Image: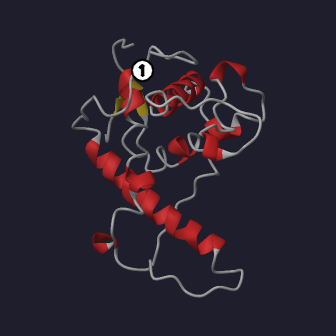
Amino acid sequence: NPQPVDTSNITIPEKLEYFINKYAEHSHDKWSMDKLANGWIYGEIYSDSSKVQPLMKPYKLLSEKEKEIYRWPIKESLKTMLAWGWRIERTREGDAAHGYSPRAIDMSNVTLSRDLHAMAEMMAENYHNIWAKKKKLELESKGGGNHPLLVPYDTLTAKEKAKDREKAQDILKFLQINGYAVSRG
């Protein structure tokens, strides 16, 4: 049986509010640096055959409504992170074409730490078990049939886990780039 967690009952920390904005900015820099080897730009007509997208909006010009693309994936990264009682502590300090060109890096060139990996794979299993209730939310109450993703955990293929386990490693990586202590005790 898929075992859900309660996310939306905890209040957002104000001490991590500098982290949320800076990580949403750096997530825009990473996401567009996956698009700056090619050159995707904002456009008015959403006809993707001309390789133009209606999402390539800069981070420095967000309203309080277009931040929903940048807020709603990231705020779920904290509501289940502090669910097992594991808190976040502090460490020492840590830091051709044009367009919105970042002086930033990606999220595949740093290594993970030893107090981090058990949290990382526990959060990956937790994402597998909350998206299992999300797939019980979309196409089983409208009129469809059953869906065969009710298997035990250690057998299901990982091509459906690509947006699930590779979101569980960068959310603790920017805690190391900003210098936040991860601790299981």
Front one among 60 and 118: 60
Please provide percent x and percent y for residue 15.
Answer: 56, 24
Please provide percent x and percent y for residue 96.
Answer: 44, 15
* Coloration of the structure image: secondary structure
Looking at the image, which residue is at 28% across and 70% down? 154
Circle 1 — which element?
loop
Q: Is residue 68 left or right of residue 129?
A: right
Q: Is residue 16 left or right of residue 58?
A: left
Please provide percent x and percent y for residue 175.
Answer: 41, 28
Q: Is residue 62 left or right of residue 134?
A: right
The relative height of residue 161 versus residue 87 in the rendered view (above or below) is below
Q: Residue furthest left?
A: 114
Of the 4 image quadrants, the one containing the C terminus is top left
Structural crowding at the residue carrying mark 1, measured as other residues with C-alpha within 10 Å and reported as few (<14), some (14–19) or many (≥20)? some
Of the 4 image quadrants, the one containing the N terminus is bottom left
Please provide percent x and percent y for residue 58.
Answer: 64, 24
Looking at the image, which residue is at 51% across and 62% down? 130
Visible in this render: residue 179? no
The relative height of residue 135 versus residue 123 in the rendered view (above or below) is below
Looking at the image, which residue is at 38% across and 28% down? 106
Total marks in image: 1
Q: Indicate the quadrant where residue 141 lies.
A: bottom right
**Residue, disc 1:** 178
Looking at the image, which residue is at 37% across and 62% down? 159
